[PDB]
Image (tube, rainbow, N blue to C red; front, side, top):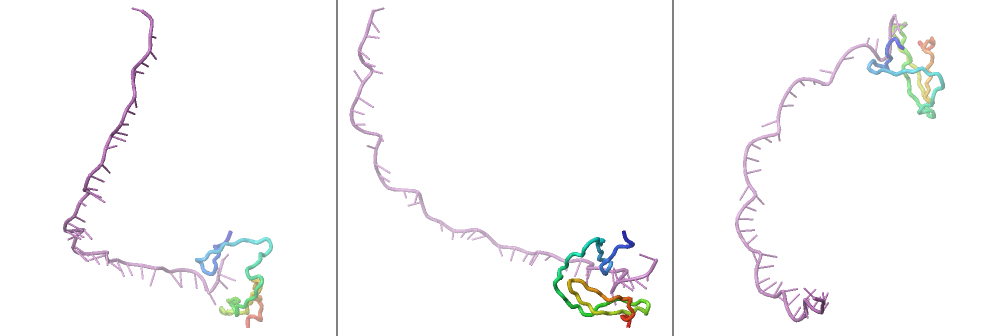
Amino acid sequence: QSFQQPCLGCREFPASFELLEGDVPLSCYAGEKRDLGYMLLDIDFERDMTPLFFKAVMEDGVITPPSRTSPEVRA
RNA sequence: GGAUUGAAACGCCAUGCUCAGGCUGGCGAGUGGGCGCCACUCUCCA
């Protein structure tokens, strides 16, 4: 069930979804590391729609952004 | 039931492959070659 059909960015791109109850499978670049540069973290609606950026790096195809609620990132 | 740099967003209207031209004039299948040599229907019952 759902409140509405999810989309991959734009409404013309629907997404099929599933719930996982087990282990994460392997990934295509499981044994490679890669750099992305800076990326968008989130948008601050409360302080008049202000964006935030952070540093992105991929290794084993897993990326771990910092918490967007953390105050220090709001500078 | 606030917010996926999102919520809305046509590649569209229409256009001849056309007019016309001979595969034609003409050339012998023709000269001549034995089906021949010889062979019992024949031996019986008023």
